[PDB]
Image (spheres, coloured by chain):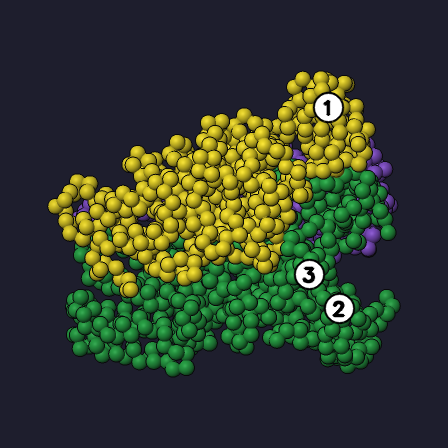
Chain colours: A green, B purple, C yellow
C-alpha cells in the first residue's frame, strides 16, 4: 500500500523514507530483490530496518514495502515432519520452487502447503458458543499425530456454519458470528513468534518424565514442563543421548531447533532423525517432529529467531493438550548470534560482549516452556519440556550464557569427555550434574511405586559422593591401606557405575529401562551393600564376601539386560542374603 | 489531553513533541493505533519535547496513529491496611484475582529520607527461630541483615523459613511480613506463594511478585513498592514489618540492563555506577523512628558470586548493611539445613539486641566461646586433610566430634523446625 | 559509464564521493588519479547521493579535485574458467605468471551462496594423501576440513607441499585438483611453494592465489574467498574433487583485526572484531559435498601453533568450526622425524567415513585401533625410564619401547617426497604390528 524508498545501506542496516504507515517490528521487503528485514527504529517517516539476508548490491532509491505484520509462523496442517529454516521457510519446497541447491537472496515462500487437500472432520455442533482454544474440528495430518483445529485468539461468538469435507488450509471451514461482525475461520492461524501464546494458568511441573535412561530418570530427573541444560563436549555421545530422549520420552511431539550449527552436523541431523523408529507405532520419528535447520553461515537474524519460531510451534501443540519437547542444539550459537547482532548495532555491552539483555532474553524463552492449562471450556492441560544444549567454545562452564541459563532452569546434565574416554555411556558427570526436581520426583515415584524409592536414590547418591571422597584418599594411600568397610562401599559404587549408570543405547533391551525395572535393579545393588555391611558387622572379612558371591553379582551386572516382560531381578535379593548367611 | 505527536521510537524509548507541563519521571499511557494501552515513564524532558520509556516495549506501535497521555504523577502505591493477605505484582497491581483495594492514599515509591536526629536506635530482638542466626548473628528490629548464597543451595528455603517463624517476644504488637520477589522464576514464586498459603503466614503478609520474564524496568520499581508498603504499615499503623527481598542480584542485573538501554555512561563492570546510591536508598529505608511505634527490618537475599566478581558486589551491600549471613554449597551437600557458615557470618548489631532483659543471660557468653569450639574444631580436621590420621589426634580429640555436632544437629535444624531461643540455648549447652 | 569528479573527502584509506546515484553496497570502484594512476576499491557505505569507499592501495598521493571515480557496477568477482589449472594469480585473481590472460566463462561473486542444509551431502569417502601417519590413523575424508597446527620453521610448509603433491583419489576421480591460497606469507615461503609445484609438475593440476605479507590486508581478506570460489566452480560445475590449502590463516585473523581497526569499529577481545567467528565460518562452511553431484571441496587450513597458553581468538575460533586437529611438534623435527606429526592429539572425527571395503583394505579400522594404544604405551615405556632404567619392568613394557621408537623410525618418518600408497601404508603397518606377540592384541583375524 505504501512504497518506502531506501536512503541508506550500511552493513546489515537499511534506512528507508516514506514508511509512516508501518509499525515497529513489522517485517518488510527491502530493495529490488525484496530481501527480508525487520523494522527496529522509526524517526518521523524514516524507518531503520534490520535486514535478515545479505545486503550486498543494494543501494538508495530502491523500494521498501512492509508485510503489515511481525515475524510470524503459520500454524496448521502441513507442519509436522517438515524441515524449516529459522523463519519457517520450507527447505524442500525451497529447492523445488527455486530449482536450486542454494538459498538465494530475497525469495519469499509460504511455510505450509496451501494447495494440499486435507480431510477436516467437524467435532462441534452447529450453533455452539465457543471461545479461543476451543477445538472446532480435527485433521489426521500424520500417521501418528492428530491436528486439532482450534479457535484463534481474539475470536468469540457462536459457531454459525461448520461442515466437514476436503479443504486446503485457505478454505473457510467455519463461520462464527461475533459482536464485531461475521468472521470466517480456516485450518491455519498465524502467530508472532516473539509473543508467548496465551494460556489460562501456569502450573507446577511435578510429574517426572520417563526418558528410559536410568542415570537421569533416577538421579537427575526432569519433569513434564521442566527445562534441562546439557553441556556437550566433543566426542561425548551427546548426539545419541539427545536421540534417546527424543525417541523414548513419553511426549507427544518433538521440536528440534538448529540454532546455527556446522552444516555437516546439521545434515547428520537431517539424515538420522527420519531413521529413528517410534517404539509405540514403528513409524518414523519425523512423523512426530518439527525440525528447524540453521547453519553457521546462514543469516545471523534467522539463527537468532530460530528458537522463537521453535518455541512458538511448541506452544501451538501444547495448546492442543499435547506434551511437547523442544530441543535447542545449541543455545550457545543462538547467543553468539544475539551478541553479534547487538555489537553490530553499537549497543552497550554486557559480560564478555554479550548484550545487557542476554539474561532477560533467556528468561523470556525458558519461561515460555512449562506445564499449563490451555484455553477452552474443557480446560485441557499441556506442557513444553525444554532440553537445551549449551556448548561454549571456551571449555569453561563459567560463561554468561551457561550461568544465565542455569539460574532459570532446574536440572543440569553435565556431559564429560573424560568420562566418555573411560567408556562410560551416557557420559554424564554424576557429581557435578544436578536436578532440583529430585525431591518432588521422589514424592511422586514413592507414591506410585509404593516403596522407599526416594530413600534409595538418596543413598545411592550418598555412597557415590562418598566414593569421590574415598577415591581421593586412595590416591594418597593405596586401596590396601584403607578400612575393610570403605572398600565395600567402593565396590558397591562400582556396581552403581557399571551395572546402573552405564547403558548401551543400541542394545535392544538396554536402550530403555522402565520405572519398575530401574527400581528392582537399584534395589538389588543397594541390598548388596546392606547385607554385606551386616556381614562386616558380624566380623567377616570383605575379601571373603567378594569371593563367595561371585556368580550372583555377575547376574547383577547382567541385570540391565533382562527383558521387560519377565522380571527375574527380584529373586536376586534373596540369593544375596542366603549366600552371605553361608559365609557367616 | 492526549498528544498525537510521537516523532521517534528507538528501542524501548519514545520521543514526544509539542508537549508542555511534562515533568521528569512522570507516568504516561500510550494508546496504540489498535486500542492497546501501555504504561510508561518520562526519563528526559527538554523544551517542548519529552523522552519516555514504555514498560511493555514498543513492538507493534505505529507512531503516526498512536497517542500519549501524561498522567501528571510518578509511580505510586495505593496503600491501605487491607493489603494484608493480598498478592500483587512488581507494580502493586493485583496478582491474586481478589477483591479490589480502595486506597487510603497514593504514595511516591521513592520515599523520604529520615532526618538522622529523628531516627531511633535498633533495640529489640527478633527470634528467627534459626539458632545459627538468633545466637551467633542476632537479628534486631530496624536492622538490615542480608543473606548470601549459591543457586539452589536452599537460600530461598531459608528465606521462606524466616518469613514463617519470625516473631517478637511480647507479640502484643503484630509482626507483618512484606515479601518482594525480584526477577525470580514462576516456580520459585510458586514455592513462596503456596508455602505462604499452606502455613497460613499469608494472613500477615503483603507480597510483591516480579518474575524473571517481567520487564526489567518494573523489576527496578518492585523493591521500592515493597518498601513503601512496609513504611506505611510501620509508621502509619504502628506495625513491626519484616521485609524479605529475593533476589537482589537480579535487581543489580536489571539496573545494568536499563542503564545500557538508555545509552548512559557505564561504571564498574558495566554496572550503572550508581549501585551504591540505589542500593543504599533501598537499604537505608529500614529502622525505627523516635516517637512512633512501628519498625522496618530488611533481610535482602543475594546470589553469591562464586566466580570472577561480575556480581552485585556484596562489599557495596555489606558496606551499607549491618551484617552478612553466608550459605555455602559444602554445607548443602552434607545435608545441613540451613547451611549457614557461622565463621564469615556477622551481625554488626547483635550487641544491644541481646542482653539482660532481652534474652536469657547465658546467651552472650556461650556465643562468644561457642564460636571457639567450631574455630578450633575445623582448625584441625579440615586444614589437616593430609595429616588427618594422627596430627593433633591424641589431644584435641573431641574438638572434631563436637564440630560435627554443630553442623549435624545445632545448625542442621531442618527447613521446617522452629527453635525457640531458650530451646536453642539448651541445645547449645548440651553440645558443650 | 559513471565517472565522477566529485571527491569530497579523504580520511586515511577512506574516500567520500557525493552527487552520485545508482550506487550499491559493496560495489567496486575505480579511482583515476590526477597522474594517470588507477587504484581500485569497494564501497563500504552508501547514503542518499553519497558513497564511502575504501581504496585497496591506500590514498597516498591522491589530489581530490583533479581525480575521478568510476563505479564498476559489480562486487568482487572471480572470472572463472577451466583454464585456471596450471595458472598462478595474486590475491585478487590477477594473473601473476606472465601467461595469457584468461577469458572467463563467467564471473562469480567470491562470497558464494549458502547451501540448503537438506541439499548438503555428508563426507563419506577416502583420499590418497600419501601420508601414512594421517591416511591410516588421522584419515582425511572428501568434504572434510582438517587444519594443521605447527610451530614456525618445523616443516609445516613442507607438509603442505607434499599433501598438495601426493593427494589423489583412487576410484575414477574426475580430476583431483589443488587450489592453493597463500595468506600473507613472505616472498621466500611463497617462492618455495611455487617452485616446488613446478619441479614436480604439481602445477599441472593446481590453481594458485598468492597474497604476500606486504600486500594490502584487505586483499588478504579477499584471498580465501577467491580460492574457494574457484574451488566450488571446479567441484560443483566441472565435477572435480578439489583440495584447498590455505597457509597461515593466522594472518587472516590479523588482517581482519587491522581492517576492523581502520574502519572505526567496536573491538572484541584483543582488538579482534565482533564478527571474527562468523567470517571464519563463512569460509569453513564452504567445504563438503552436494547431493546428486560428483564434485567435492576439502579444506586443509594451515595455521601456526600459538605460543601463549591463553589461545588467541584465532585457534579457539577455528576450533569448533573444524572437524579435527592435526599437530606438529618441534620435538620430532629435531628428533629426525621429518613430518613432525605427533599422532597422540591428532584426530579426524570423520575417519570412519574414509575406511572400509571399496574404500580401502578392510583391516583399516582394527589395525589403526591397535596402533594408537601401542604407540601410547610404548611412549609410556620410554618415559617410564625416568630414574627407573632397564631393570625396572624389563618385560612387556620394554618390548613396547622398541615398537614406539621404530614407529617413528619409518612409519612416521616417511620422506617429504615419498608417496606411500594406502596398500603400502597398511602392509608396512601389519609388518610393524608383527613386532609384539599375538597375545597383546585382543584383535582376531
Q: Chain of mark 3?
A: A
- The answer to whether marks 2 and 1 mark residues whose Cβ atoms lie closer than 8 Å is no
Q: Is residue A225 above or below residue C70?
A: below
Task: Tell me the SS state at disc 2.
Answer: loop
Neighbour class for label 1 at 10 Å: few (<14), some, many (≥20)?
many
A478 on left or right of B197: left
* Along the viewing direction, whichever of A485 and A47 lies nearer the viewer: A47
Q: Position of residue A170 (x, y in %)?
A: 78, 68
Same chain, labels 3 and 2? yes
Q: Which mark is residue A153?
A: none
C139 on left or right of A127: left
Please name the residue shown 42% across and 54% down the image. C351
A14 on left or right of A303: right
Q: Chain of mark 1?
A: C
Q: Position of residue A575 (x, y in %)?
A: 26, 79
Q: Position of residue C343 (x, y in %)?
A: 35, 46
Task: Tell me the SS state at disc 3.
Answer: helix
Circle 1 residue: C32
Say which quarter of the image contains residue A137: bottom right
* Along the viewing direction, whichever of A453 and B238 lies nearer the viewer: A453
Q: Which mark is residue A96?
A: 3
| Whole-number angstrom distance, CA of label 1 to CA of label 3 | 46 Å
Circle 2 residue: A115
Neighbour class for label 3 at 10 Å: few (<14), some, many (≥20)?
few
| Whole-number angstrom distance, CA of label 2 to CA of label 1 | 57 Å
Please name the residue shown 64% across and 48% down the image. C113
- The answer to whether marks 1 and 3 mark residues whose Cβ atoms lie closer than 8 Å is no
Please name the residue shown 84% across and 72% down the image. A177
Q: Is residue C190 above or below residue A446?
A: above
Amino acid at each position: 500500500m505504501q512504497i518506502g524508498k531506501i536512503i541508506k545501506v550500511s552493513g546489515p542496516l537499511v534506512m528507508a523514507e516514506n514508511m509512516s504507515e508501518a509499525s515497529i517490528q513489522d517485517m518488510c521487503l527491502v530493495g529490488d530483490l525484496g530481501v527480508i528485514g525487520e523494522i527496529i527504529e522509526m524517526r518521523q517517516d524514516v524507518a531503520s530496518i534490520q535486514v535478515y539476508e545479505e545486503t550486498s548490491g543494494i543501494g538508495p532509491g530502491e523500494p521498501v514495502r512492509s508485510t503489515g505484520e511481525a515475524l510470524s509462523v503459520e500454524l496448521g496442517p502441513g507442519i509436522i515432519s517438515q524441515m524449516f529454516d529459522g523463519i519457517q521457510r520450507p527447505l524442500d519446497t525451497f529447492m523445488e520452487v527455486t530449482q536450486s541447491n542454494f538459498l538465494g537472496r530475497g525469495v519469499q515462500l509460504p511455510a505450509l502447503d496451501h494447495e494440499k487437500q486435507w480431510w477436516f472432520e467437524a467435532t462441534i455442533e452447529e450453533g455452539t458458543e465457543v471461545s479461543a482454544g476451543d477445538i472446532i474440528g480435527y485433521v489426521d495430518e500424520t500417521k501418528i499425530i492428530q491436528h486439532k483445529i482450534m479457535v484463534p485468539n481474539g475470536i468469540k461468538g457462536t459457531v454459525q456454519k461448520i461442515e466437514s469435507g476436503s479443504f486446503t488450509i485457505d478454505d473457510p471451514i467455519c463461520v462464527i458470528e461475533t459482536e464485531q461482525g461475521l468472521k470466517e475461520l480456516t485450518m491455519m492461524q498465524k502467530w508472532p513468534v516473539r509473543r508467548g501464546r496465551p494460556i489460562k494458568q501456569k502450573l507446577n511441573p511435578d510429574v517426572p518424565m520417563i526418558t528410559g535412561q536410568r542415570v537421569i530418570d533416577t538421579f537427575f530427573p526432569v519433569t513434564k514442563g521442566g527445562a534441562a541444560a546439557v553441556p556437550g563436549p566433543f566426542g561425548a555421545g551427546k548426539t545419541v543421548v539427545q536421540h534417546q530422549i527424543a525417541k523414548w520420552s513419553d511426549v507427544d511431539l518433538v521440536v528440534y531447533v538448529g540454532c546455527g550449527e556446522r552444516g555437516n552436523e546439521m545434515t547428520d541431523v537431517v539424515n538420522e532423525f527420519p531413521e529413528l523408529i517410534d517404539p509405540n507405532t514403528g513409524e518414523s520419528l519425523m512423523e512426530r517432529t518439527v525440525l528447524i535447520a540453521n547453519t553457521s553461515n546462514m543469516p545471523v537474524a534467522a539463527r537468532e529467531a530460530s528458537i522463537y519460531t521453535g518455541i512458538t510451534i511448541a506452544e501451538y501443540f501444547r495448546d492442543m493438550g499435547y506434551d511437547v519437547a523442544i530441543m535447542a542444539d545449541s543455545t550457545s550459537r543462538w547467543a553468539e548470534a544475539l551478541r553479534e547482532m547487538s555489537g553490530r548495532l553499537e549497543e552497550m555491552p554486557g559480560d564478555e560482549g554479550y548484550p545487557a539483555y542476554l539474561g532477560s532474553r533467556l528468561a523470556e524463552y525458558y519461561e515460555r516452556s512449562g506445564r499449563v492449562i490451555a484455553l477452552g471450556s474443557d480446560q485441557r492441560e499441556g506442557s513444553i519440556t525444554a532440553i537445551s544444549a549449551v556448548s561454549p567454545s571456551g571449555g569453561d562452564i563459567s560463561e554468561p550464557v551457561t550461568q544465565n541459563t542455569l539460574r532459570v532452569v532446574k536440572v543440569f546434565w553435565g556431559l564429560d569427555s573424560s568420562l566418555a574416554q573411560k567408556r562410560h555411556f551416557p557420559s554424564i558427570n554424576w557429581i557435578q550434574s544436578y536436578s532440583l526436581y529430585s525431591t518432588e520426583v521422589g514424592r511422586y515415584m514413592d507414591q506410585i511405586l509404593q516403596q522407599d524409592w526416594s530413600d534409595m536414590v538418596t543413598e545411592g547418591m550418598r555412597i557415590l559422593q562418598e566414593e569421590e571422597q574415598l577415591n581421593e584418599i586412595v590416591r594418597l594411600v593405596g586401596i590396601d591401606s584403607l578400612s575393610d568397610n570403605d572398600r565395600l562401599t567402593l565396590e558397591v559404587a562400582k556396581s552403581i557405575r557399571e551395572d546402573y549408570l552405564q547403558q548401551n543405547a543400541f542394545d535392544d533391551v538396554d536402550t530403555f529401562t522402565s520405572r519398575e525395572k530401574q527400581f528392582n535393579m537399584l534395589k538389588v545393588i543397594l541390598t548388596f551393600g546392606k547385607e554385606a555391611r551386616k556381614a562386616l558387622s558380624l566380623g567377616a572379612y570383605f575379601n571373603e564376601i567378594m569371593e563367595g558371591t561371585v556368580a550372583v553379582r555377575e547376574r547383577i551386572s547382567r541385570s540391565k539386560y533382562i527383558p521387560e516382560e519377565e522380571l527375574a531381578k527380584i529373586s536376586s535379593i534373596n540369593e544375596e542374603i542366603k549366600e552371605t548367611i553361608q559365609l557367616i | 489531553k492526549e498528544y498525537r505527536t510521537i516523532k521517534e521510537v528507538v528501542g524501548p524509548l519514545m520521543a514526544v513533541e509539542k508537549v508542555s507541563g511534562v515533568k521528569y519521571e512522570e507516568l504516561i499511557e500510550v494508546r496504540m493505533q489498535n486500542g492497546e494501552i501501555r504504561r510508561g515513564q518520562v526519563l528526559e524532558v527538554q523544551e517542548d519535547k519529552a523522552m519516555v520509556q514504555i514498560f511493555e516495549g514498543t513492538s507493534g506501535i505505529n507512531l503516526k496513529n498512536s497517542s500519549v497521555r501524561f498522567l501528571g504523577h510518578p509511580l505510586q502505591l495505593g496503600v491501605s491496611e487491607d493489603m494484608i493477605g493480598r498478592v500483587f505484582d512488581g507494580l502493586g497491581r493485583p496478582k491474586d484475582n481478589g477483591p479490589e483495594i480502595l486506597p487510603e492514599k497514593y504514595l511516591d515509591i521513592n520515599g523520604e529520607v529520615i532526618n538522622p536526629i529523628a531516627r531511633d536506635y535498633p533495640d529489640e530482638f527478633i527470634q528467627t527461630g534459626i539458632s545459627a542466626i538468633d545466637h551467633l548473628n542476632t537479628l534486631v528490629r530496624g536492622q538490615k541483615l542480608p543473606v548470601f548464597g549459591p543457586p539452589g543451595a536452599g537460600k530461598s528455603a531459608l528465606a521462606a523459613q524466616i518469613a514463617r517463624q519470625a516473631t517478637v517476644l511480647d507479640s502484643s504488637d503484630d509482626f507483618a511480613v512484606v515479601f518482594a520477589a525480584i526477577g525470580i522464576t514462576f516456580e520459585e514464586a510458586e514455592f513462596f506463594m503456596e508455602d505462604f498459603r499452606q502455613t497460613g503466614a499469608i494472613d500477615r503478609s503483603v507480597m510483591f511478585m516480579n518474575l524473571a520474564n517481567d520487564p526489567a524496568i518494573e523489576r527496578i520499581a518492585t523493591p521500592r513498592m515493597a518498601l513503601t508498603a512496609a513504611e506505611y504499615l510501620a509508621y502509619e499503623k504502628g506495625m513491626h514489618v519484616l521485609v524479605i527481598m529475593e533476589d537482589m542480584t537480579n535487581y543489580a542485573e536489571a539496573l545494568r540492563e536499563i542503564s545500557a538501554a538508555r545509552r548512559e555512561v557505564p561504571g564498574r563492570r558495566g554496572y550503572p555506577g550508581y549501585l551504591y546510591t540505589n542500593l543504599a536508598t533501598l537499604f537505608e529505608r529500614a529502622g525505627r523512628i523516635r516517637g512512633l511505634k512501628g519498625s522496618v527490618t530488611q533481610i535482602p537475599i543475594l546470589t553469591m558470586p562464586e566466580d570472577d566478581k561480575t556480581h552485585p558486589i556484596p562489599d557495596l551491600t555489606g558496606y551499607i548493611t549491618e551484617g552478612q549471613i553466608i550459605l555455602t554449597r559444602e554445607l548443602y551437600k552434607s545435608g545441613i539445613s540451613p547451611p549457614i557458615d557461622v565463621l564469615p557470618s556477622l551481625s554488626r548489631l547483635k550487641d544491644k539486641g541481646t542482653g539482660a532483659g532481652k534474652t536469657r543471660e547465658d546467651h552472650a557468653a556461650t556465643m562468644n566461646q561457642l564460636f571457639a569450639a567450631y574455630a578450633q574444631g575445623k582448625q584441625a580436621k579440615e586444614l589437616a586433610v593430609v595429616l588427618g590420621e594422627s596430627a593433633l589426634s591424641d589431644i584435641d580429640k573431641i574438638y572434631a566430634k563436637f564440630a560435627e555436632r554443630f553442623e549435624n544437629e545445632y545448625v542442621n535444624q531442618g527447613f521446617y523446625t522452629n527453635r525457640t531461643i531458650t530451646e536453642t540455648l539448651d541445645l547449645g549447652w548440651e553440645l558443650l
